[PDB]
Image 1 (cartoon, each protein chain N blue to C red):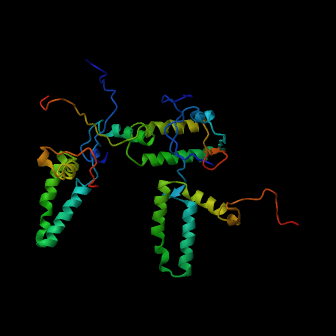
Image 2: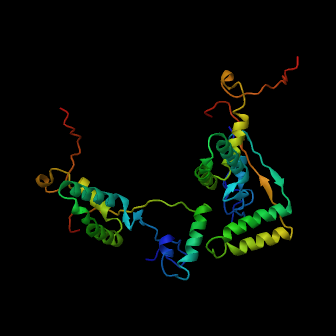
Length: 104
Length: 104
Length: 96
Length: 48
């Protein structure tokens, strides 16, 4: 059927949605992760390796511009469905209902 | 008679129609055909023959600008009505209805 | 099987999610509105204004719309917030 | 838009029309597509 529809009276929705706080067009938290990683590489192997910044930084800008919140999804997956140990045994990631906190 | 007419309320039609993907104002596929042909000429007879590019390239730009999709019509004709063998016997290009695929 | 909304449009027509009331599939819709401070909301809207105004001058979508948007937000007529909607359909077999 | 704006500034056909065109297309009000119309008339003799 046709429940209530629009006739240009619809309440405006502005596209300031998910315009995340970005510097150079990239969010703070993932760019800081890249800074930490490249700093680790620079301190570990060689010091010529702050040239690893612009390539991955540009690829991250292209990723963020297309799909503004990819990194939050990435971190959620990594934290939850990647940590869960017995993925293989169950055929799927499962959490026991009864609270077996290793106590007795 | 006069079926429904216009009163400037007509839905806009923009002239992005058949603005084909063009480099220098010429579509990719025919220009690549010219590149292949001129490369063949250059490799075959003489190497001074990448001067054959600008004349025919300019004539192709003038052809495309006037009539944006001449090359598609050209290729369709060449593929179908030019290949059909028995044009002379029938007085016209004809395809047999019964599927004689040379089998028995 | 969960699902997610990620792309709005130039509209907030009332009750646009009515169509999932008449469903043949038993589900659980969800929402969230983490109400947000007036300075932070004004900053988000200022960010949208800045991004938009750093471009070609669209006649009306550009200027007056965000004029009235910001003026309402200061004059207390709406309160921005962080939102997410996750329709999850329940079923008996994975194909279904 | 680019081809049009690479020219003299027509007052209204140029700017606002493609402004609203692109804004609708993003806001989901029409979907472009590739189109061709071929009227074929049937008859009994080639003159007709």
